[PDB]
Image 1 (spheres, rainbow, N blue to C red):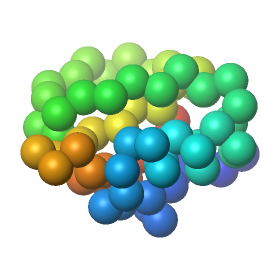
Image 2: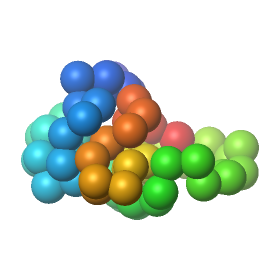
Image 3: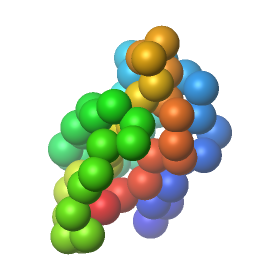
Length: 64
């Protein structure tokens, strides 16, 4: 189980989702502005995409 996609930093949401869904077809993908405060709960189904103001991936996407 691959759980992180560092190679997607700087990519658009559209591009990132295409790669993630190949690896984890039933992923629950949520998009949030980078810096958003989140809780510590671990959700194995989820992959949060933290984006910058240009709508590009700003932090390494990971399961959780």
